[PDB]
Image (spheres, coloured by chain):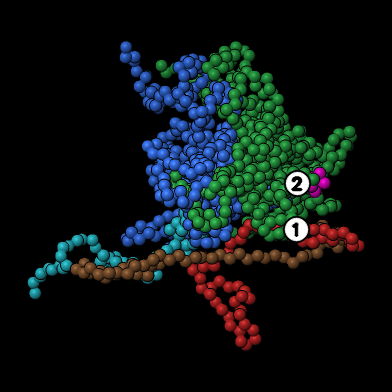
Chain colours: A cyan, B blue, C green, D red, E brown
Amino acid sequence: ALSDLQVFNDWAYKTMSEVLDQQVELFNGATRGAIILRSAGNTGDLSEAAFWA
Amino acid sequence: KYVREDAKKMHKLWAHIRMAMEGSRAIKDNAKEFVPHPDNTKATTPEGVARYKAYIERAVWYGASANTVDGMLGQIFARDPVFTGPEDKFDMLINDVDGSGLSIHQQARDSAEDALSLGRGGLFVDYSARPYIKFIAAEDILNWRERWVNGAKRTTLLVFREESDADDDGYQIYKEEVWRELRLVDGTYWQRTWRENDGQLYVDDWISPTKADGSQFDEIPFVIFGSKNNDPTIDMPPMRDLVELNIAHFRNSADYEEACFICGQPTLFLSGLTEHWVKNVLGGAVVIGSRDAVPLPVNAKPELLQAEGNGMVKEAMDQKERQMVALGAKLIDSDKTQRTFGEASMEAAAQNSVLSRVSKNVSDAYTKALRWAAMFLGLDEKIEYELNSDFDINKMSPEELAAVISAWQSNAISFTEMRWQIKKGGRAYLEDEDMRNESEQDDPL
Amino acid sequence: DSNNIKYVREDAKKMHKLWAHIRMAMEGSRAIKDNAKEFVPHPDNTKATTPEGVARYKAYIERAVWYGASANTVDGMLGQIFARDPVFTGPEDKFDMLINDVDGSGLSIHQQARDSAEDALSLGRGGLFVDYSARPYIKFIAAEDILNWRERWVNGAKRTTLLVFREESDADDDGYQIYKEEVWRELRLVDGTYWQRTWRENDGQLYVDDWISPTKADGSQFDEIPFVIFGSKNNDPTIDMPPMRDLVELNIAHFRNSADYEEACFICGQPTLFLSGLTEHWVKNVLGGAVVIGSRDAVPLPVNAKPELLQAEGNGMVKEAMDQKERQMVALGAKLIDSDKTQRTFGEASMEAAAQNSVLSRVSKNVSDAYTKALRWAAMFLGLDEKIEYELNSDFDINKMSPEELAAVISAWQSNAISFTEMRWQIKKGGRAYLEDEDMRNESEQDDPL
Amino acid sequence: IIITDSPALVSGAAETLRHSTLGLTTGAILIEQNQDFDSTVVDGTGKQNITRQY
Amino acid sequence: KIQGLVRPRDPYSNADVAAKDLRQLVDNTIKVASGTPPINIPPSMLRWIQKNP
């Protein structure tokens, strides 16, 4: 993969941090909507919705 | 003997120049390579590394190289570079030279600083439809060839590193790379591109770009401009010895600051003192203010000792500051010294030698890039892009105005040339066409 | 048919050391410190045998300071000789391909002329080669690459019988893989005919070309070898001594003095207490191996103890030698460095300007003649007009022209004394115009719009 | 499958040979030359013929 | 890499949590030196059969 050992713009300038080894791109379209990643806050420690039976 | 040039070993020199340009921080986090440790025995020990940290932190970085480049750019880039040819047709090249809305003048300024700092750069005119005049850093160019075919110096191969960042759904920082691959077979231009996905090099087949009419291409659309000349060979950076002087001054300043911190404060040095007298009257506490006087035993000589000035360290520091000014690099101004007007007129040519060389080199490089862009779009070829070849420009004098108009009334200078004279002299801002449109009407009176 | 294609005439072998020294002086601190053994004498070779001796020498060299006034001199002279641009007299649309890409690599003739004049200023030797592939090209051959030549008197005429030069090249193999292949060209003149062989060594095998005579567009082959040796002195095959030698010597001496000065400043520069009239008993009584020297803390000493804070004084002999060497470098008249403290009376340098810009004038005329001859050779290759010229910037100490100068030039042009093209060239010289002569004539032919 | 007869890959002999194949990612093996190539031809005298040495 | 950068905190609780430190792993690029055994190329053997040295 990327090495960037050739040029050192700065010392360890974002060159590597072994950021992660597991595939984690599984959200929204990546999971075809199966695992939807959203951003909408709600209060308390729950979120209750009611629908008819 | 010795190898050609430096055997293309300007990598460390470019790194050092970039660190010097960055400022005091880059030099200070690089003190190990610049400032030698005073003692290696300490250097191994932990008290030694603490001592070296205290030694370097107290130092002062002068930072004259950045001022040198800033002054050179200011002298080169006054008003705006002149463009010759159809301005209406090339406006969509000038305004957004590479699709970002950045004007060609600002990219020219960036390339000029790259030429002045480490003496290397690169222009790459690619076709997306709209031609794009790229700018490639010195470290990105990582291969070039000089196979001469048909008895002519030709550049056949050139590969440069091309940088980009990916905006994936997650703001996760994704650094992916592209390697453009320029080749010249039988005097014909071919290219291939690589896309890298965290180490997934997807190679593309060799392709043959063509001009608007056709006929493909005869030479690679890539020019390597340097301070010396626009040649693929590595040209020496203009500020090599300048960085050496700055680094030497920095280490001398480190020594000077250690001296100032330690021995700069005077001390009593109560010689001929007996501990019995101390415990009798001094009591382990000496009051030195002018309200109180301290008594001493027989034949004791107090004496204030402080390191004085005009030492050899500050002598060397003043010598190196003089050396920088002596070099002639427009880095600092001296209020103390004065120079008669007209004496510097003779040496103005020599002082601005690197300025003129870089100006002409970058002007030729951008002219060639514009020719290639016009070839891609099938426009006119007689286009030029000349930077300001007249440095030290100032507000032109009223007698100089009289001379300029008197010269224009005679048929020795064009109207556009006269307007460029006035504009460069800081006496007008409106375009010549606009002034003509406004002044073609009857007089107000 | 021929002897070894590489054979260095002993003069070039002798001059190789000086050329390498001058080249490395142009290089800067890096080359000098990489090869310090040749310049900076070892303070004690008895140490140099030992490993701590080589460590001492490395530490004593890395602290040195390289002035490099020679690089600045070359730059200044080059800027003065190539302020503005050289002018070309003759057909321009016909010769435009020799102007834009003089060797087929998009390098304008002005840049190549600048580089050749730079080598003339530094090493005092160069060479232009004109060959035919189709279109002719003008090559540039460095001083080191011209490795042999020959002069014969045939019919009382000094003729260059042989001139072989090593033309450096590169191999673009299938991959991106660094190969460095060389091409040697032998130029011969037999029975008044120019003959040419290339030792191609492509693929690392025998591709030596035969007896071939490049021929003009009309024919008749050639009467003289199309290769010119331009130098600081004149256009001779014989060696012209470099104009940079004495400055390089002075910079090397200043470098060694700077190394000595830096060692002295690093060692003896810091002040030192030098406590005297002391005893170990008192030291362990009070000092305890740690002396506080801040202003807020005082330290006593026993009877007849005299502290003497010592440091190396200024204006030492080393600075005196370094200063005289810098002043000598300036005295030579070279534009290496300047001094704002000094002052010069205007109008006094007007008498010595001829003597100060000597080397500049000599290299200007030499390179101008070399490029004129090369352009004539190319014209004969393509059968164009022969009376063409390439006149470098002869006038030095260039400056923006005065309103008085502008008025005088315009007055001279209106009189039948100075030509219109001459006036336009002068105006361009002083930075008062940028458009071409024909362009301005076309634009200004029309009456004033008012 | 890039193919080369590298003795570093045969890793065996006779019937106890063990051929070895290695799959790589981009930049797996990085070989950096130092741009320091020196060729020297030194001559010697004293023999029946002049000798050279590359 | 910091092994644990995510932990199941309980906002209803206030308990001590251990600390972690940033390590520093070094990369390496060894230098390999190669050469050529001395090769005899006397000119006599080549000029004896009319070949350039």
**Residue B303: x and y, percent?**
51, 40
Residue at the spot 39% in from the left edge and 36% down from the top edge:
B290
Residues shaded magenta: C8-13
Q: Position of residue A38 (x, y in %)?
A: 24, 63
Which numbered marker is on residue B368? none
Q: Nearer the viewer, mark 1 or mark 2?
A: 2
What subunit carries mark 1? D
Q: Residue at x 84, y 40 (%)?
A: C151
Query: Magenta part mainly helix, strand or loop?
Result: helix
Question: Is B45 located above or below residue C10 in the figure?
Answer: below
- Answer with left or right where residue B54 lies relative to residue C354: left
Give the chain letter at badge 2.
C
What amino acid is at disc 2?
A: Lys
Distance of label 1 from label 2 (alpha carbons): 17 Å
Q: How far across and how far down the image is residue B306, in percent?
A: 51, 41
The residue beneath circle 1 is D40
Q: Is residue C134 above or below residue B76?
A: below
Give the amino acid type for the residue marked by disc 1 in the picture. Thr
Q: Are marks 1 and 2 on the same chain?
A: no
Badge 2 marks a residue whose secondary structure is helix
Lateral position of residue C303 relative to residue B282, left or right = right
Residue at image mark 2: C17
Tell which of B392 and C256 is nearer to you.
C256
